[PDB]
Amino acid sequence: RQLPNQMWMQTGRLSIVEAARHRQSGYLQLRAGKPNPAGGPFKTSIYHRPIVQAELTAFCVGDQQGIEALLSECRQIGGKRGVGFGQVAGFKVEPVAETDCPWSWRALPADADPRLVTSEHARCIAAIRGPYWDRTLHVEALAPTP
Amino acid sequence: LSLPHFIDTLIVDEAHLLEQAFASVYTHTLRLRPLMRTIEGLDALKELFTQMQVATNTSLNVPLSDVPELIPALKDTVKTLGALPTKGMSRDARSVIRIATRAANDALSGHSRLRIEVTPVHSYPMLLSGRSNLQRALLGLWNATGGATLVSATLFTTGDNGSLTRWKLEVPTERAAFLPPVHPAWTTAPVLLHKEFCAHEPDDSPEWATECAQTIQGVASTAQGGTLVLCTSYQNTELLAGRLGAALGDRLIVQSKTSSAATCLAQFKAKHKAGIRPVWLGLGAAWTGIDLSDHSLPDNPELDRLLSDLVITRIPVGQNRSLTHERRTAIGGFRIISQEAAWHFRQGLGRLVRRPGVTHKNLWVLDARIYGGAAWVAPFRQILDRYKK
Amino acid sequence: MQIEVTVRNITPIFSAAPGSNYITIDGTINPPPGVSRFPLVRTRMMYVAADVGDGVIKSVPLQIVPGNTMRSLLRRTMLKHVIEPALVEKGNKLSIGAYATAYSGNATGNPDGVPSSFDEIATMRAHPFIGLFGGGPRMLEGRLMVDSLYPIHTNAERILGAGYENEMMSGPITQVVWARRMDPILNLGSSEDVEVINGGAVAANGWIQDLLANSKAAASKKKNGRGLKAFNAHEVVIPGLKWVWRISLDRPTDAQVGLVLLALNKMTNERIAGGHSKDYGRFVIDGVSLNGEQVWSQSGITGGEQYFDAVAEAIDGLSSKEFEQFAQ
Amino acid sequence: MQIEVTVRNITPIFSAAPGSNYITIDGTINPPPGVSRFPLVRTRMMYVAADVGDGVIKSVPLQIVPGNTMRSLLRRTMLKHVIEPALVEKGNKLSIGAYATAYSGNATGNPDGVPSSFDEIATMRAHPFIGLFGGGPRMLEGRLMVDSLYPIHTNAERILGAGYENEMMSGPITQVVWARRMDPILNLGSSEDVEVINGGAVAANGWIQDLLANSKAAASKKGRGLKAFNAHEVVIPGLKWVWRISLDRPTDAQVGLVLLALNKMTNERIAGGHSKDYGRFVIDGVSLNGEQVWSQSGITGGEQYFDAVAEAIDGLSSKEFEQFAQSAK
Amino acid sequence: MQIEVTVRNITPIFSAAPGSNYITIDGTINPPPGVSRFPLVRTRMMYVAADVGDGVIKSVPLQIVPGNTMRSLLRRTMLKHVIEPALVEKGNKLSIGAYATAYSGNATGNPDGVPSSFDEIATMRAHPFIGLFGGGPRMLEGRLMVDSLYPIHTNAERILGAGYENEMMSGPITQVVWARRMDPILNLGSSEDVEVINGGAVAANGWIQDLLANSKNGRGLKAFNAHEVVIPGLKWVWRISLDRPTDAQVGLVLLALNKMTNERIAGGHSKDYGRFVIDGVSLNGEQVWSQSGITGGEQYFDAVAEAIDGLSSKEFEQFAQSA
DNA sequence: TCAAGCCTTCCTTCAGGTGTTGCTCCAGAAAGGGTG
DNA sequence: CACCCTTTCATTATTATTATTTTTTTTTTTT
């Protein structure tokens, strides 16, 4: 963390005034004569997400040139939000020795090797591969805590 | 007329100076005493001097803020200087008359700043019509350049940041290209950085002058060759001269209003040739742009001992007083003052190593702010973090 | 491709922030308890990294407009200025859930998770409006990445990047504008001013005793209703400030970029604020750079005629069945 | 609709600013502790980014009237000159909460969190008056955008549009004006004068005894007395100002109502200091969406707006203000 | 209602400027330190916006009688001249707080933090006097707007232009007037003049000894100082505006304007500085002044004549009472 | 052509602001009903 | 059955909040 972990707020609401003028103009076909800020299309929603400005360091085994070619397009990281967050100032890949690198700090299967399981790993439901947001692919995994 | 209308490839040597050259070009200055001696060989210019007197900052960065009698006096100056008969007036006098009228016509428009300075010889009347904004002309050079390489010895701020550099030369950001610099180890290898310093803070005081001069006496006693002691002002170097005169005798060289950098440099070669060990109370051009590597031994730099000691007496803050730097400082703030001081100090430290192969080089910093707990001298420490022991 | 819009706000900028912020009458933000305080809604500010000062990174406040406000403003000006006249010159009637998907980022077309084939993903991402944002139950990634409105400020030099050092601000950029509401019954002068009130003098007097009783009861409780007499504060970003706006499009078509350009052609009538009553957030556009090349002129956009022809033939051909098929 | 009215203030302009602000006798504003410091209410300052010198965009103070004050003045001008005069011409009357919503937007604190109806929002935003200022217990967006009144000044070039570079002032626009509260009974020059004051001489001498006790208490310390010596910063008169009154998708009648207000802006005070005639103005021009439609008699142009507002105020009734005014909860 | 009175000051006008000004022997105002400078207060000054080069507008100082000064002057010249005779002849007798609120507009510097009931505000805005000035502890807004007295100048042309181009005057309007307080024990120089002294010649000589000791914080009677006046004879206008006046209130202001002649613009009393003669009164653009007084406008005088009759102090007592 | 100003005054007490002034709302969605 | 109204239920509880302290040089080789 270069910065303290602050918070971002965002809200969502459809503009009711333009909806009313479109309902009169005929461009909107709305049978309901009243909105609802607690639910529905005109719901106002407030939501707060943590915000961190940080140096992000990962460890992996692979070809540096391909990672550079992939990360050249990487304009954002953490959220591909399309709203402006996580813009990459830069990236850097260096080779390091074997005993320094903690590859093991990763979501692992429960049948992993005894030298690969650490203390901060614990048994849970997590994705270990591919789309980590897809809960249908989530498996019984041993994973580290951020 | 003298250069092609479109430059396909432009390479600038020592690009750090180049903007100042533009700042040299777009100042048109009216010199009063050569005019007054030329006309004798009007009373309106004397009234311009009398109204010029009423206006330590004398009207800095003010294009037209105060003009009580400045513009009718300028108009009378223009009309009494341009209507003098060209027939019978001398061939070298018309140069003075024409540069004075060009400077006055630059002054009249109101698109330029006005500055006052006096000569080092005496309190002569010097007046300047200069341009503090320089985006238009240099941008008119960059659309006229296809590609350019700007090479310098202090071009970059910190690592790969050169943002203020493309601010000074007004380089377009789309055409800017920031390459990694080359900072070899042999520039920092033979140089030895000493822990001792002057405990008094530099505050233009005589007690600081005595304690600092006792440290110069220590360094000159331990010097196996020449010593350059760098200052930023005339007053502190005259304080150091008055504190080191009877102490050092013929070993010292001072720079003043009557002692230029070239004369001092020539004396430095002269009494290094005589075998004595000189010290040099240097300022101004002694910071940036002097060759203190000897040309009597080209092939063998391991016997180079012309300058065995560089001592920096104070951090060079407040050195750049130009119109463009004042305007750029007013936008940026304290940061531009700190980074320009870093570039001046890097040019000051670059006088030690000019070629690889030299040995037994000594570097001294006596500013007590450097070794203090202040955070504003933080870059000044990291450059001193490139030396060890 | 990238569009950078440099604008100056004619009026102040106010985008309200969460939390309970209190200011004294002098100006001290967030006082310790035991002293009189004041309600304050500051403009939205993020703590950003700063290499100014030292080489180490320090956390500095930076007062912005959030990027969501930018995204919705760009969206709403495309709907209000080019999309709606095209759809009402044809006679199209949107549905709620398709109107909610086009005008908001909401999934009330079907709250259910609608499956999206890759061919229909491709045919909706190539739509001149729809593929910019997406939204709805498909939850497909829109092509438009709209950044926050960043002021050209020294706290944002990491966000702004090099090149904005000329024409740059520093120091404080927020002013705490104090506003108030007076009870207008106290403003009532005479019988001619009060004759429009049902009851008139009796009703005005009754409200005055009601307000007096409520205020003295509240002050006696200090040693749950509320009156009209209010006096509060809100931090705004200073007017006349220069702002950069980054709009990066992930593999766009010509019609999508043309729609963004025609949004910038007509966004002078739009506002960016939580101050719509006070005309806050009025701005004029000073520069629009496409792929690093500036294109904005004083008489709208001059350049990118291929984008203009593409967006003309795009907004001519739409018949709003694609909006309905995008919703459900 | 983007109305641009350029005004000329005949008298000074005083929109006071909150805060514990002090001034010395010679004029040192906000002086440090340990010196003689005096109360001062500064006028409304807006920090504006400006081009001081060459480049150097910096936050310099301009002196304004806020958009709330100017907007309220517009609200009061069309109300007290067009709306309620033509509304008491027949038997239409409002409730006192409807008066409160017509003058301050809302009728109470703690407004209800329920939304307003779509057809209700639509018919109020098409109203000649209610659509310009939509408050109420259910928040409604006002069609009227009213910008702060800016002096035509060189600190506001990044605020002001083109074509106003001429007739345009520069330099400081304020003056500190000093008002001293003078106890009136020390001006009493005879017992002829004291007859009307109670008790004859005894109550006047009792107030002198009272003043002496308060003076001794304040001096030995170093209620409250009647001496009220103070100074207030004003914006100097004769200035030309710009005022921008925008209307997003306006009805013809609403623009006609703002036009009739601008035609009846005479003898109105802008900001504050009502006792000292502060805020009297003579509007030099109105710019209706780029066109100049002011002569010194009045508007005398754009007959569609005046006809629209005329047929609007003939059909004006109070029931729109009531259905704007009742709380849903 | 618009009231545009046209006065020409017969005497120099001096309205004291707060601060600490200084002047040399000559007209150099606020000298740099080192030269012997004399204390000086100036005429109260207001910057205008005016065109210096006939196209360029600049803040230029103009010397004025302030609006609050003329507001207090109007309060004094209606209160003593018509309000006090109506109170005296009916035997109506105010209180001390009522008198303070009748002049200062506030009985006490502390106001009560309450609003008044509307029937009260309507009654006192119906008042010919209290409706004009308002005030009180509950802050009644008055019906009278009193502007500063403006000399018809180049500077005031952007202030005033309703037919004031020809008789507009150009040039500076100020003058420095000096005053020395001499110790008059240094001027008697006689035994006939010292017989009035209790103690006599020895007492006078002892005062000279104290003057000898103090001349090289007991400050003696010596003083040399100056004050800046407006010149006499130039012609000014005054804006008096009424927001929603009753006919009684405007009749009271008209009756003030009819007896405005023997009153001093508040200023330097002993030098007779405030003297002026009304050249005209424009009444919504209608000139209704004559050399005898105010011709025409009889309904306003009739309304204030009925207004003055039946005047009672019970409203002045109610207005001054706090919570 | 000489005279071509000498001295001394350099402001004194006042003059402290008072009231109000603390935000308001909400950012739920499954429950039955009712209507085309 | 898609379009809405309007009902209904829920258990603990507290409140902290980043903002700054230059020196005054005379270079350079243009028209």
Image (cartoon, coloured by chain):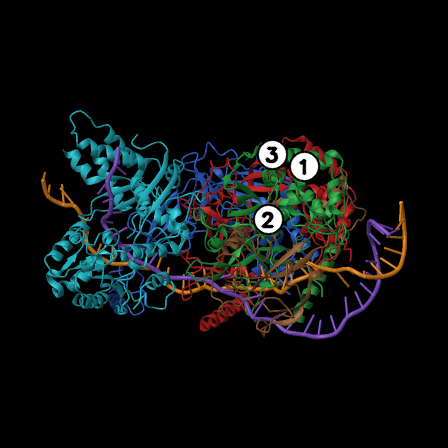
Chain colours: A brown, B cyan, C green, D red, E blue, F orange, G purple
Q: Which residue is denoted by mark 2 in the rendering?
A: C145
Question: Does residue D115 appear to the left or right of E35 in the view shown?
Answer: right
CA separation in Å, label 3 and label 1: 36 Å
CA separation in Å, label 2 and label 3: 21 Å
**Residue B77, position as x, y percentages in the image:** 26, 34
Q: Quadrant of residue E18?
A: bottom left
Question: Does residue E71 appear to the left or right of C123 in the view shown?
Answer: left
Label 2 Cα neighbours within 10 Å, binned few <14 / some 14-19 / many ≥20: many
The kind of residue on which mark 1 rests is Gly
The reply to whether callout 3 and callout 1 are in contact (CB within 8 Å) is: no
The answer to whether A139 is drawn above or below residue B293 in the figure is: below
Q: Depth check: give the residue in front, B253 or D63.
A: B253
The kind of residue on which mark 2 rests is Met
**Residue B167, position as x, y percentages in the image:** 40, 47
| Labels 1 and 2 share a subunit | no
**Residue D66, position as x, y percentages in the image:** 57, 49
Q: Residue at the location (46% across, 46% down)? A: D50
* Helix, strand or loop at mark 2: strand
The answer to whether G22 is drawn above or below residue E47 in the figure is: below
Q: Chain of mark 3?
A: C
Q: Which residue is denoted by mark 1 in the rendering?
A: D256
| Mark carried by residue C58 | none
Label 3 Cα neighbours within 10 Å, binned few <14 / some 14-19 / many ≥20: some
* Helix, strand or loop at mark 3: helix
The kind of residue on which mark 3 rests is Phe
Q: Depth check: give the residue in front, E16 or B384.
A: B384
**Residue C266, position as x, y percentages in the image:** 61, 38
The answer to whether B372 is drawn above or below residue C50 in the figure is: below
Quadrant occupied by the N terminus of chain E = top right
Residue D87 seen in render: no
Q: Which residue is denoted by mark 3 in the rendering?
A: C308
Q: Residue at the location (26% across, 52% down)? A: B288
